[PDB]
Length: 158
Length: 145
Ligand SMILES: O=C(O)C[C@@H](Cc1ccccc1)[C@H](O)SCc1ccccc1
Ligand SMILES: O=C(O)C[C@@H](Cc1ccccc1)[C@H](O)SCc1ccccc1
Ligand SMILES: [Zn+2]
Ligand SMILES: [Zn+2]
Image 1 (tube, rainbow over the protein chains, first blue to last red):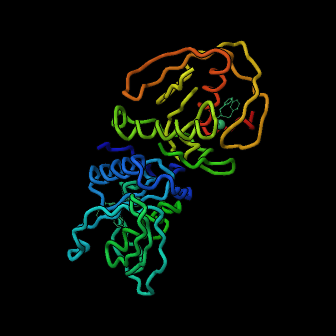
Image 2: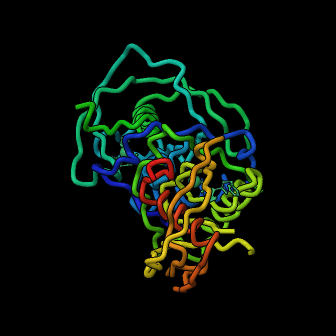
Image 3: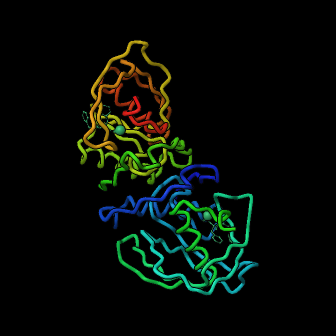
């Protein structure tokens, strides 16, 4: 497993709209190795999520994990979910502020208003369609990672 | 092997300075799979070279086709003051063709996929292709020449 270099705020890769993964990439050693290298990168930095743009890959691939911490002690321990072409279908009206950091903004942490719950549809690495509702810290991480795919850093939301 | 979608002129990705490949990535399954997908994409499009930004990867990896050479972190160290005009096309600017003045000889330092430093000189057509692909790593399309 490879740890990849991470783009920092100021780098233009972080401001693009990432390109969808095409059907012929699904269920490929190419997509498995990309997910594996993203996963190894997130763990090396003690992250709970990562988006492909952060490792200079302008593609719609994110990982969402969760672990309990100071700010959310009842946050689940959740192993990496790889989400290909994730789409948030619905944001809850209920909104709560929560502590965020970013691998691309290692200097700063902040309070961000996020939907308490999001309905998300995505493809597995195999190309299987999944629809899940995320709540709480994992909802926040999914919103943060989709923002990365859309060229948005959390500091722009404070 | 995977054929990757190709960025077209107008996409911001083609206008960045691609990031160097890190020592971590050298001799990795990740880097071989990247080179294979780039190679498959080039062949499927009938191309004679490709750069990683063209497949939405902002990394300094190019292929030049002679059997294809993959070059990681290439740098043009030496070139002829003597220029040649050759017809160019681009996978990222479909159905566009133009004469571009290039150095007729280039000496290129690069890493292999295994991560050993190597030097090669290209003349003529492969020299034009190297210069075109290094331009892609620096956010330049051939139309701007
Ligand atoms: O930059 C990233 O995408 C990784 C962030 C994800 C994140 C999103 C929302 C809320 C918190 C984190 C990294 O995990 S930052 C490190 C971190 C870890 C746990 C809690 C807070 C910050
Ligand atoms: O955009 C690319 O990098 C791929 C081009 C490379 C090229 C650079 C300089 C001169 C010619 C080609 C593709 O091979 S374009 C298709 C093509 C093939 C043979 C001759 C001309 C154009
Ligand atoms: Zn982030
Ligand atoms: Zn080109």
